[PDB]
Image (cartoon, coloured by chain):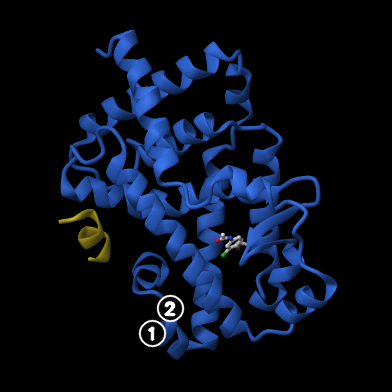
Amino acid sequence: YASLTEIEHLVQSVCKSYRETCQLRLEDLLRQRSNIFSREEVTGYQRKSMWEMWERCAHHLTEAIQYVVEFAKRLSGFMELCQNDQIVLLKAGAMEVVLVRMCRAYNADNRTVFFEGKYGGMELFRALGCSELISSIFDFSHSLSALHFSEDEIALYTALVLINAHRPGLQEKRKVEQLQYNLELAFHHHLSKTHRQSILAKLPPKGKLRSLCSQHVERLQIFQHLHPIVVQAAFPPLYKELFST
Amino acid sequence: TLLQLLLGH
Ligand SMILES: CCOc1ccc(NC(C)=O)cc1Cl
């Protein structure tokens, strides 16, 4: 039965955990907005091989996932959960948190995302051969950017994307339920202080994040068919563990 | 698993 003071402290703690495990500082991200890939550089990426483009993207996603694991490790109550549940939560949610986190690196003015040093549009990713997935990812980020999240709101929202008591396989279910509820209280408390509670009805329906992760696993099945050795030899082992079927 | 090791288990 968390007090209002304990809830306020939870807001601060989560926001701190997030800031500390942010890959990119928001100021650096902003100071690079006009730094956009040229026609020539975009052509360079489009001309790359499928295997090369996948290998690069797999590396970047894995790096992002590493930061999310660190976020979990610093998140109030997460490390108090049993080993099984920490794993169940991360397996189901790490990619979802990365997808939400991406909106920090997404400039909605020109529909570009910070990728390998500059801002590129989704046409940079053509060689992947998964345009519906890539475009779905860009649309998700765009729809999120329409909410104009603050760093604090992202911190709280991602905590909730991760701490989901309905993940199949949890063993201390009531313990996860309690953490999710307190995080919901913290989120709703922070929103009301800023009169931003209206965003809640505008958050992505959970099916959306699920369809994105599912598309990624499917497109990887197809890539792996075409290039079985690349995955074993070149892809980060964590990536392989989390996404290969 | 790798997740376990990363969690410090
Ligand atoms: C279409 C999704 O692809 C990406 C977009 C942006 C980044 N950026 C960073 C900094 O990792 C990485 C990937 Cl794999």
Q: x, y percentage for residue A84?
A: 19, 50
Question: Would you name the residue on which mark 2 appears?
Answer: A235
The reply, left or right, for residue A159 in relation to residue A176 is right
Disc 2 residue crowd, few under 14, some 14–19, many 20+, Cα 10 Å: some
Q: Chain of mark 1?
A: A
Q: Quadrant of the N terminus of chain A?
A: top left
Tell me what residue is drawn at x 56 percent, y 76 percent: A54
Amino acid carrying label 2: it is Phe
Tell me what residue is drawn at x 33 percent, y 19 percent: A9
Could you tell me if the residues under marks 2 and 1 are in contact, i.e. CB atoms within 8 Å? yes
Amino acid carrying label 1: it is Gln
Q: Nearer the viewer, residue A232 or A104?
A: A104
The colour with which the image depicts chain B is yellow
Tell me what residue is drawn at x 49 percent, y 71 percent: A58
Q: Quadrant of ligand 1?
A: bottom right
Q: x, y percentage for residue A156?
A: 45, 31
The colour with which the image depicts chain A is blue
Disc 1 residue crowd, few under 14, some 14–19, many 20+, Cα 10 Å: few
Question: Would you name the residue on which mark 1 appears?
Answer: A232
From the viewer's perspective, is residue A95 above or below residue A5?
A: below
Figure label count: 2
Q: Are marks 2 and 1 on the same chain?
A: yes
Q: x, y percentage for residue A91?
A: 34, 55
The reply, left or right, for residue A21 in relation to residue A135 is left
From the viewer's perspective, is residue B1 above or below residue A14?
A: below
Q: Quadrant of the C terminus of chain A?
A: bottom left
